[PDB]
Length: 131
Length: 131
Image (cartoon, rainbow over all chains, first blue to last red; front, side, top):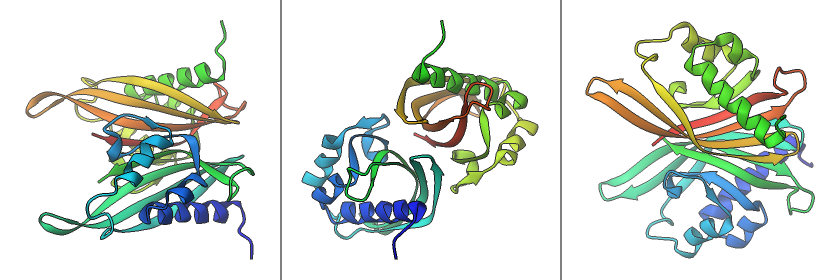
């Protein structure tokens, strides 16, 4: 059974998390616009732009990124023409110096229709912020 | 001289800040979609929806919200059809128990074209997160 627009973007959004979690850069590029912008903890407080910024973290995965477990919670999509706004809570289990920890992030992901992209959608902007 | 699409949304985005800063609820409603969603510190970690949530803060402005000074820094817009993604850094001067303080927020504002709205644009989602 094929997914409608809203279900479809949710699936691609989930697939992107899988790609990031597994360090699959090639997969990342099938879903993310070359001129993607973002606010995220790793971006040091300013808007980061382009894939090169993100590839840096793929090329230098360290040190216990493999122990990490990430899940998306409470996902929702809102459609505005060819734009889809996906909102969710990202919960990350990781190990720190003090032991196992859990952190929650608010995530906004803005997806745009593009039949040229593998799944018919591309990520153009996202905003992730920690609790 | 009239503003093009990108300049136009930046102006409306600035006007919205002016409305919030001055507690002008009527102005707020000329710019913000009735089904607006948001992530923001005031939303207690989950996605808030609707104008009623925001009106609560207008109706209960307290206690030194008038002393506050807010400015937008490094604004940028990206256009995707009828969607405009405005990104900016929000700097807020306020007084705490310990004295005058300054805080920076990352802000994503998603605006959508609508000729029915006063300025031709409506805010449908935003994401604000503190440093």
